[PDB]
Each structure stands twice: as structure tokens, then as C-alpha cells.
């Protein structure tokens, strides 16, 4: 549920 904006910046392809 929580946002993944952070996880995105450190998980882009």
C-alpha cells in the first residue's frame, strides 16, 4: 500500500 517512489529511484531499468 505504501509508496514506492524511493524503491523506484533505486530500482530503475
Image (tube, helix red, strand yellow):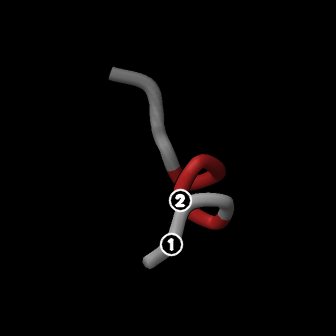
Extreme residue toward the top, this view: 1
- Mark number for residue 12? 1
Please identify the quadrant where the C terminus is shown.
bottom left
| Eye-nearest disc, 2 or 1 | 1
Image height of 2 relative to 4, above or below:
above
Query: Looking at the image, how many numbered discs can be counted on the residues?
Result: 2
Residue at the spot 64% in from the left edge and 66% down from the top edge: 9
Q: Under tag 2, what secondary structure?
A: helix
Image height of 12 relative to 8, above or below:
below
- Mark number for residue 8? 2
Residue at the spot 49% in from the left edge and 43% down from the top edge: 4
For the residue pair 9 and 3, the one nearer the viewer reads as 9
CA gap between label 2 and label 1 equals 6 Å
The crowding category of the residue bearing disc 1, from other C-alpha atoms within 10 Å (few below 14, some 14 to 19, many at least 20), is few
Residue at the spot 32% in from the left edge and 21% down from the top edge: 1
Image height of 11 relative to 7, above or below:
below
Q: Under tag 1, what secondary structure?
A: loop
Residues at marks 2 and 1 touching, judged by CB atoms closer than 8 Å: yes
Amino acid at each position: 500500500f505504501l509508496p514506492l517512489w524511493l524503491w523506484l529511484w533505486r530500482k530503475l531499468k
